[PDB]
Structure formats: C-alpha cells, structure tokens
Image (cartoon, coloured by chain):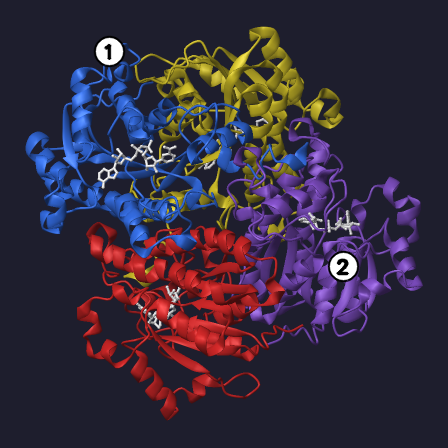
Chain colours: A blue, B purple, C red, D yellow
Amino acid sequence: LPIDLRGKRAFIAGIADDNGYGWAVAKSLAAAGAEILVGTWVPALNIFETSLRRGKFDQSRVLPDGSLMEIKKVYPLDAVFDNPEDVPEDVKANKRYAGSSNWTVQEAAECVRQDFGSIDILVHSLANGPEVSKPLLETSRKGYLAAISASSYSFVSLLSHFLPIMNPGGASISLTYIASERIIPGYGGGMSSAKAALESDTRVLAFEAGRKQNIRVNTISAGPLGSRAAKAIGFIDTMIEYSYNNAPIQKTLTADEVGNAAAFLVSPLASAITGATIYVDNGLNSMGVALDSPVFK
Amino acid sequence: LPIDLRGKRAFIAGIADDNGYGWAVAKSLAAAGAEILVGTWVPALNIFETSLRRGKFDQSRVLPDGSLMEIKKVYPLDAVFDNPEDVPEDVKANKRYAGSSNWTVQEAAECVRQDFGSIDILVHSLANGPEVSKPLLETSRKGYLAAISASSYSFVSLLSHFLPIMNPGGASISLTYIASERIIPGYGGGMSSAKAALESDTRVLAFEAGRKQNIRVNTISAGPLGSRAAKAIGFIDTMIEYSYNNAPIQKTLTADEVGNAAAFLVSPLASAITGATIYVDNGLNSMGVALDSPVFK
Amino acid sequence: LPIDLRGKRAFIAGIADDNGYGWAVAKSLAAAGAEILVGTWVPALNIFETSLRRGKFDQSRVLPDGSLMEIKKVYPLDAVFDNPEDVPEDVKANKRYAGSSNWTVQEAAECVRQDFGSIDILVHSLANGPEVSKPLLETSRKGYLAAISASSYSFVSLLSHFLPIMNPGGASISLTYIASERIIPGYGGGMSSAKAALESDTRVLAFEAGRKQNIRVNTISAGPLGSRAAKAIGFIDTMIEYSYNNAPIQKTLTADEVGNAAAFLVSPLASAITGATIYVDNGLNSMGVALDSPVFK
Amino acid sequence: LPIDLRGKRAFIAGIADDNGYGWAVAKSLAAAGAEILVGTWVPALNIFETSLRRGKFDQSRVLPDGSLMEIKKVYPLDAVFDNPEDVPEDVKANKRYAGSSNWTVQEAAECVRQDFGSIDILVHSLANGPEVSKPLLETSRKGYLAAISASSYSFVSLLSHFLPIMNPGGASISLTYIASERIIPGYGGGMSSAKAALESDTRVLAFEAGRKQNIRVNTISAGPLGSRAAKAIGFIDTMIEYSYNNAPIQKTLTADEVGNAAAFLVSPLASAITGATIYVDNGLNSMGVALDSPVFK
Ligand SMILES: NC(=O)c1ccc[n+]([C@@H]2O[C@H](COP(=O)([O-])OP(=O)(O)OC[C@H]3O[C@@H](n4cnc5c(N)ncnc54)[C@H](O)[C@@H]3O)[C@@H](O)[C@H]2O)c1
Ligand SMILES: NC(=O)c1ccc[n+]([C@@H]2O[C@H](COP(=O)([O-])OP(=O)(O)OC[C@H]3O[C@@H](n4cnc5c(N)ncnc54)[C@H](O)[C@@H]3O)[C@@H](O)[C@H]2O)c1
Ligand SMILES: NC(=O)c1ccc[n+]([C@@H]2O[C@H](COP(=O)([O-])OP(=O)(O)OC[C@H]3O[C@@H](n4cnc5c(N)ncnc54)[C@H](O)[C@@H]3O)[C@@H](O)[C@H]2O)c1
Ligand SMILES: NC(=O)c1ccc[n+]([C@@H]2O[C@H](COP(=O)([O-])OP(=O)(O)OC[C@H]3O[C@@H](n4cnc5c(N)ncnc54)[C@H](O)[C@@H]3O)[C@@H](O)[C@H]2O)c1
C-alpha cells in the first residue's frame, strides 16, 4: 500500500536550501517516485545551485532506499511578479535579477510547458513578510500588502498559471500556520492575515479547480519545524519549546513528518480529500490550555 | 435602546442559590422586566426556599434600579426524570423526593401550564457529573451516561416538554464550556462530552424549533466564573487564574457578565441570531498560546 | 436593562446612504444615545451631505422613540490612503478629491481629535473590490490586493490611528461575511480573502488593543441584507432568496437586526466579549444542507 | 514511499459484512500488511462467519496485489457491555448471545491478549441508534442514551480496555459524520449528538493516551458511502445524490477512499497527526451553499 507517484511530476515553489519544509516535501515526493522540478527565489538561486553542484546537500538528499534525490531542473522565480511588464525597472536592474531570465510566474510556467509539457502536482512552500517582526498595530500598509502578496496571492497566481498544464486528477498543496485561526503573538507584519487568506483560498480554489479540471486543493497547517535550542531565543526556538511541552504527544516535529503527509495528500490515495486544512503539528492546535502554565503546579 | 422583556416570562432551570450563572441570568432577565419562574433541584429545594424566606439572598437580589428581584414561583425538579413512571422506587422513597411532588420534567411543565398558561423564555443552567473528577480513560459507562443525561439530554427534554407552551418568537438559552471543542485536562467524567452534545443539539434544535414554532435556540460558552483565590487550588480556582493571566483582555469574569449576554440573546433585539455558540469568556478561546508559559520570558 | 451609550461617541466609517449596514448601526448607536460622527467616502460625500440637507433621509432617520437621528459631523475619508504623502498626484487632482481636504486616515483622525478630543466606539463598515465579479482563478494581483487594502487593512489603519484617542473600555466592531470560512461561489475578486483576513485580525487586534488600552474587538458575520426580489437576479438577490428558504428560522434579515447586535456589542453589557465572530444571519451558517435542494422532495 | 504495517496488528471493531466502511479499512490495513483481528456484533456473528466460510465475500477480499484478504480471527462482541456483570439476564438468555461467549469489551480484550499478546492499531467502526429516525424533539431519553452508549462511549471503553495491550507508537481511528458540527436533518435519535461526543473525546483521548502511552488518536469525518440510486429514496440515497451534485469535486465516494485515508493515519507516516477530525467527503463540508438550489438557475 504505497504512495506511488511514479510517472508523475511536481513543481515545487520555494526551495532555497535543504533546511525548510519545501526541501522535505520534495524528498517525500521523490521517495514516492515523482519527477522533481524546482522553483528557486531568484536572489537565492545561485548559492543554491552552487552548493548543490558542490555536493553540499548530499547528506540531505538521501532517500530511504538509500538512493539520492534528483532535481530534474531548477527554475528561477519571484512569485510577486506575474508578467514581465510588472517588474520595476529597478528590480530588473539588480545584479541578481540581471543574471537570470524567465522568472515571472507567467514565464516559469511557459518554460515548464515548453520543457515538460505537463505536471501533476503543485507545491507551494513560499512566504515572505518584511515587517513580520511588528505587531499589526505597527504594521505599515505596504508591509502588510507585501506579506499578502508574496504569501497568499502567489498561490493563486501559480495555480492559475499552471492549471492549463496540470493533468486532471492532479493536486496542489500549500503550507499554513495556525496563527490564522488563533492568536500567536510574535507572528506579525500581516503574516497571520496572509495565512488566513491562503486558507480560505484553498477552499475556494478547491471549488474552482475541482470543477474546472478535477484538481484537488489542500493546505497543511504545520508546527514549528525543528528540534530544541540550548537557548530558545527568538520566535521559532520559543514555539518549538512551547510545543514540545504543551502538545498532546510530547515530541519534536521533523520535516520528514510534514513531507510524508504532503506526499500522501497529493497522491491518488487521497482522492476524496479537498478544501482541507490538515494539521500536522503534534496535535497542539487541539489543546485548550498550556500544560506549562505556572498556575497548574 | 433597551432590552425589554416586559410582559414576558422565563422559566429558569438550575437555580439552587445565589452563586451560579443561573442566579445571574435570572437577575438579568428580571432587570429587563421578565416574570421569573424557577426550577430547583429537588434535593436542594428546601434550603433554597428557606434561605430565600429568611432574607439570606437579599443582597444578591438587588437590581440595578435598586429594587429587589422577585421569584414568582419555585418549582421543584429533577431533569434526569421525564415522566413519573421513570422514577426508581428507591428515589421516590428518599426523604427529599418524598417531600415534594410534580418534579418530573413532564410534571413541572404541566404545572406551569396550569399556573401561567405560557412562557416566552427558557433557560437551562443545569449540569451534573458524578465522575467529573476522573479522566475519560477512567470514566465508567454509567458515570459517562449520567453526565450526558443530566447535562445534555435534560435540555432536549425541557425544550420538548415546554415547546407546546412557548409563545412563538420566544427563545431558549443554555450554558456551555469550551472543553467541548478543546482539551481542558481536569474537566472529566464525560462533562466534556456532554458539553459537546449540548452544542450540537443547540444547532439541530434551532432548526427543529425554529421551523416548528419560531423559537430561537442559542448557547453561551462561558469562562470560569469568579474572582481569584488566595490559593488557587482545585480546578475552577486554577482556571480563573489561568484565564486572568492569558486572556486577550486581562480581567476577571462576573456572573453579571454572563447574565447580560443571556438577557440580550433571549431578547427581541436578537431576532437574527440562532444555532450559535457565543463566547463570553474574555476572549480566551481565541488565544493560540498561554502568555504565562515559562518559555516566553 | 438598557443599552446605554449616553455620553459616548462613535466614529462610523462607511456611510454613504441610508441603505447599508452602516446606516443601520448608526441608527442603533444613536437610539442607545451615542454621539454620532461619520466618515464618508470622499467620491460619495457630496451626494450624501446634499440629500441629508434636503431631507431625503428623513424617514430613514426615525428612531424608535420617534425622534430623528442626528449626525454631529460628517468627515470625508478614503481608507486606502493613510498619510497624505501616499496619495497619487492623479488622485489628488480628481475633481472629487480636489473638493475636500483632510481625507486620509491619519488626517481624519487628527481632525476628530481636534474637534472632539476622544471617542469610545469604532465602527468599520467599509469594503470595496474592483474584480469582485471574477473568480479567484481570474482575479488579477492588483484587483486582489485592492480588495484586501480597502476591505481588510483599512480596519487595521483606522484602529491604529484612532487608538490614541479611544477611551479605554471602548470597543470597535466590523462587518464580515461567511465567504471567509466557506465556499460561496459568486463572491470573488479577493473579497472572500479579504473577509478572512479581517476576521483573523479581529482576533489579533483584540489581543493587541485589549492589552494595550482595554479595548474590545469584535466582528459580526452578517447575512444578505434585504427583502426579496420579484426576480432574484444578481448575487445579493439570489442569497437573500436562498437564505430565506434554507435558514433554520424562515424570515428575512433587516438592517435593524444587525444594528441592534452591534449596539449591544460595543456596549458595556458586552464587557466579557472580544475576538469574536458573531453570526447574525438567521442561523444559516449552521446548516449542513440546503432544504431546497431538489434531491429532498 | 509505502504505507507499511508489516508486522503490525489491528483490531477492527464493527465488521458484519463486506458493505461498510469497516470492511474497507480492514482491506486497506491488510493491503499495507497488517495482521487483521475482527470484532463482530454478536447477533451478526453467525451469518458473518458462515458467508465467509462459504466464499460469499471472496470478491470483496481481493487486494490490489491480487491476493485475498485474511482475517486471522473473528471475535464476537457487544460494545454496550463492558463486563459480564453488566449484562441483563434477559440478554444473556437470548439465543444469539447464548451461542457465544467472551463478548464483553473486557472479555474480548482479555482474549486478544491471551491470543496475541498485543496490538498496534485500533479501529472503531461502530454505531447504532434505535430512534435514529426521529427528530431530537421526538427522541426518547432512552433512545438518546442508547445512541451515545453504542456510538460514543464504546470507543472510550475499547480504548481503555485495549490500551494496556497497545504497543506504544500505535494508533486508533474512528468514523464520524458532519451532522456533529452542522445541521443535517434526517440524522436523528441522538446520532448527531453521539457523533459530537465522539469527536470531542477524540481530542481528549489523544491527550490522555498520547501522554500515557504514545498512542495517536484520530477520527475521520466521512461522506455518504456508495454510488447513486436509480431512485434516491431514504436518507443515505438522498445524501449520496446531494453530495454528488454539490461537492467541490463531482464524484462519488468509495469505501476504498475512506480505507486508504485510515491506513495512512494509523501508519507511522502520520507520526505528527493527533486530535484530528479528517474530512474524507469530497470537500462537501467546505461549501457554503448548495449548487443545486433552485435559486441559482
Ligand atoms: N518553518 C516553520 O516552522 C513553518 C510552520 C508553518 C508553516 N510554515 C510555512 O512553510 C512555508 C515554507 O517553509 P519554511 O519556512 O520551512 O521555508 P522557507 O523559510 O525557505 O520558506 C520561504 C521560501 O520562499 C522563498 N521565497 C520568498 N519570497 C519569495 C518570492 N517573492 N518568490 C519566490 N520565492 C520566494 C524563499 O527563498 C524560501 O525558499 C511557508 O508557507 C511558511 O509559512 C513553516
Ligand atoms: N460555573 C462555571 O465556571 C461555568 C463555566 C462554563 C459553563 N458553566 C455551566 O453553567 C451551568 C450552571 O452554572 P454554574 O456551574 O454556575 O451553577 P451550578 O453549579 O449551580 O449548576 C448546576 C445546577 O444544576 C442543578 N442540578 C444538578 N443536577 C440536577 C438534576 N438532575 N435536576 C435538576 N437540577 C439539577 C444544581 O442543583 C444546580 O442548580 C452548567 O451548564 C455549567 O456547565 C459554568
Ligand atoms: N450588504 C450585505 O448583504 C453584507 C453581508 C455581509 C457583510 N456585509 C459587509 O458590510 C459592510 C458594509 O455594508 P453594506 O454592504 O450594507 O454597505 P456599503 O455597500 O455602503 O459598504 C461599502 C461602504 O464603504 C464605502 N467605501 C468604499 N471604499 C471606500 C474607501 N476606499 N474609503 C472610504 N470608504 C469607502 C462606500 O462608499 C460605502 O459606504 C462591508 O463590510 C460588507 O462586506 C454586507
Ligand atoms: N455509512 C456511511 O455513509 C457513513 C458516513 C459517516 C460515518 N459513518 C460511520 O461509519 C461507522 C460504520 O460504517 P458503516 O455505516 O459503513 O457500517 P455499519 O452500518 O456496518 O456500522 C455499524 C456496525 O456496528 C456494528 N454494531 C452495532 N451495534 C453494535 C454493538 N452494540 N456492539 C458491537 N457491534 C455493533 C454493526 O453490526 C455494524 O458492523 C459508524 O461510525 C458510522 O457512523 C458511515
């Protein structure tokens, strides 16, 4: 009873290294036999392809079977720009953006088409929020819109641009965070807002794309990725700790854990699931209180 | 813009003293001019009516206007028994149950009818759970069913028995607790389960009774009632503390607070609200983490 | 048991006429004795103040007591612009925007301050979405961002700009729609998304502002406003019909209905409610199926 | 990337034939290599084992690999009775119950232990509700309690009785229905209530058992199982039709579909998922309106 993505190909948007959720899903899709195409942020591209050439990610490419993951092709990409006319002359003039081409959503999509003709899976693992450090109360309109644009609308833009080249019976999947439904102080600059929009769109799109092309649309609401810090300082480190303490099952969360769920979800096994927000967070979201609250001892 | 329940009468099930949510709603309904009828648990009846005669609740009956609340009539009542044939000879033989009569749901309802002919508001403020101290894992089938019977089904039984005598455009309201949707360790013996059922039934009944008699059906999901203990020991004391610390608005919760919401809800002002779970818990339910978790300092 | 907003003042953002939810809440706040300040979209301002001068809204200003609603002051306002430096020379050059002044969020707020010094209630009744007619799949990035900006971020901008002048123990309230949580085909152009963000922000802000200034933050998730069309054509007309048929309580929805809930919510009676999404939609949101589905007869 | 339950054994409670969800999950678990133990209702036992002997289920036992499913052992079982002292002399005297032995939850569990020593997976596929045809308004207290007992508490009883013999890192899974969260007229007699309780308990137990033995606890909220009737008459037939029409993805639902999700969930791949209600209903739960409502054409 395997997850079989043999003869299927995925496009994974949001891979810059071996340390995020994105890398993890790729691994999983690859373990299940899918053909892997990557979309890399174009400021990040170089270092990415360079370390990959050099073998830097070799240990991070080991599959269960022991073989090594293959990335059939790396595509540069800035998901805040749909078409080329949209780019600010000042962006197209930046060294980084100067070094590559065909990096708009519309362009990436045209390439894939020209290169492979089709796809079966779409993975969104993107996000970005300039003022993510500030509270809403202190978030600028521009910093807020930026988070929404890169973190929400990007999914919409990708889905619509790739849809014409998705074989029906295909699936897409995106990564969300519970700061959409509940107050998680620290996750500011409109990221929370952006995660809320993403989720809702997940539903709508499941309708739009389900009816339109028989495509499944789902999002996975993950936990803080990683193991404990010797000194939990900063937001993520903190959440990791908090979650380790307060969750129904006491353990840490691994990328592998999120990737397997993803692979499952984009797989045929999951033919009856769409417009879902799946929690893969060690059951944290379900708790009413924190176990570690000082009142309880 | 007043809440006007002048010329309306409420039946409040679950009043044994001046210290619970039930007393609070009565006060509120009474401030708004409703005619107050009480249903008192029949083990509790005596002490109740006795202290009330004696003036023991006088300070607790003060209305805003300064006058004193009036209870038009106290009806004894055991909401685990619908009809008289249902009572175990061993219950009917107990001193307490021996002292009163017409205490089944079916009987109480017949009385009211014979005494007043009609009602407009129905308040459920009942609950009871023998093994509420044990974890589900350790809850007996009998202790579990008991919680459901007294805490869930009782609402269903009251609604159905009173419905024929409720003027259309009337409303009912019940008290719930968030341990239905989220894990709140400590609230065991099937109370959690019982609160879950109640809520769902709230919805269904809103459908059944809305369509049947133009009756609104809602539940209020409250916080731990009361102010701080010098030594928070025990479940409630603990929750009060926890909530005071961790809530979006830092303050305590008062019965008045729950009563006003109730009065509002059963009032005509609320003509577009039904099949709702209203949170009156200082916004606790909305939080993702506890502020007091030691990881955060 | 009245809703008393005597000696309180509200600022209502999003009044252009007597036909929306906004007008309704004002009425309600006014019935409860609050002092009414309006923020009018500045393209709409003129016609507004003109018809109001002329008596056009006289029948729509009748309060329950029989008297007539008073608007202490109308302030022009475009909630997509925070500070004056933000305005495009091409907007400031448009006849309409040319006729008025002090219309940025930052400016409106400064005025109020200079005119009244303070406020107690904040009402957001704003929304706008250029491509609201298109499906997400066909919504432009710009049309999507526009909906979010005018429909989501505007609340954030108002709250933050007015906060310094809100007496603690005050409240704000905004209008939402269930297309945030569930698929409602027809409500496109990112409005759905925008309603999702608003809700989430409602929660966060309740935290930010609750802790910061003892301000309550809530949103009301309303139904389609209005009575039946002889020919339900178009989105709203359709929803009205659908809701009339399928709701747990069969009736239409009136603005009065939404206004009363609002008044209640911003009132002191509601001191224990924050980070809530209150449904005032005749219980529609709670249903699992449509009664009118042809399968059921 | 397989779902590997090689060297694992499951106990499936609620198998009486090849036509329910229960049969389906067994198949799935079996495809993934788990060792299958069945708990059969003891009125149903005989016909079950008889047709199975005879080959009646042969076509229904075909695995993907082509081989045939094996049931290592069938255990009789009535999940409304925990211990033998609990049985009414009038039940133990009924032909059916007379023919078998060790059929209480406590007894079944002792047997398994004595026969296999341990288990890894626990599947609950049980339900039963005498007055399921009546509306709550017309449901008896006894008919209501019966639904809860057989449909809710049974899970609690099984979990607790099997827990001592579950290898840590194991999982349990139960089948729920959306009539718990939303009004689905027709699903009466307290089934709705019972499904609500089950879900909540799913959460709590995930806490209790997660912390206690490192066991994952989840429930799957399924759609109406089956394909279209030529004449949709009756509740299920109706729901199937309705769902086919109104769902985001237009298709029917197959048992296979629910089984695969289950297998996944009880599998190690799912190590970060617990206290979840997974929807496997073709995305129906996410919709706001019915597409087939006559208002929309
Ligand atoms: N990391 C966590 O603990 C956690 C928890 C919940 C959800 N998530 C979500 O997971 C996703 C990513 O996972 P992660 O945080 O592990 O990885 P990450 O931090 O690498 O994710 C951001 C990625 O997006 C890329 N990116 C940013 N802006 C871009 C733009 N304009 N165009 C194209 N690419 C751009 C970055 O280069 C990077 O690859 C996001 O959706 C994030 O919200 C993460
Ligand atoms: N107290 C809290 O902090 C809190 C929080 C959330 C919800 N609630 C709910 O509020 C309601 C009651 O409020 P409370 O706890 O303040 O008051 P309470 O403790 O007085 O409530 C129980 C009441 O039910 C009566 N009662 C018990 N069994 C009965 C039976 N078989 N027949 C008739 N009457 C019976 C008791 O005598 C008593 O009046 C319950 O629904 C409870 O779950 C309370
Ligand atoms: N009308 C309904 O059936 C319904 C249902 C649910 C929610 N709502 C919500 O109610 C609110 C408004 O109610 P309504 O639709 O009855 O009234 P409406 O249509 O008058 O609301 C829009 C208002 O915002 C103003 N406006 C638009 N863009 C603006 C900008 N940039 N700056 C300042 N003002 C601007 C308009 O002039 C108008 O007063 C919105 O939040 C809407 O989503 C309405
Ligand atoms: N069938 C559907 O469309 C659907 C939709 C959602 C959820 N479900 C749920 O799936 C589960 C079962 O699936 P199904 O309906 O396909 O199969 P089913 O109808 O065979 O389920 C009931 C099973 O429980 C057994 N049973 C009843 N009372 C018992 C008792 N006291 N002791 C022991 N066993 C007893 C029956 O013999 C039978 O095997 C239930 O949880 C049901 O609510 C089904």
Marking on residue B23: 2
Residue picked out by circle 1: A67
From the viewer's perspective, tell me whether residue A152 is left or right of residue D13. Answer: left
Q: Mark 2 lies on which chain?
A: B
Q: Residue at x 36, y 30 (%)?
A: D257
Mark 2, Cα crowd under 10 Å, few <14 / some 14-19 / many 20+, is: many
Residue D52 visible in the snapshot: yes
| D5 relative to C206, above or below | above
| Residue at the extreme bottom of the image, as rendered | C54
Residue D60 pos. (x, y %): 37, 21
Identified at 47% across, 43% down, the residue is: A184
Q: Nearer the viewer, mark 1 or mark 2?
A: 1
* The N terminus of chain A sits in image quarter: top left
Looking at the rendered structure, the kind of residue marked 1 is Ser
Please state the horizontal and vertical placement of residue B141, each as a whole percent of the image.
69, 31
Alpha carbons under labels 1 and 2: distance apart = 70 Å
Respond yes or no on whether mark 2 lies under 8 Å from ligand 2: no
Front residue (pair A44, C39): A44
Q: In which quarter of the image is the C terminus of chain A?
A: top right
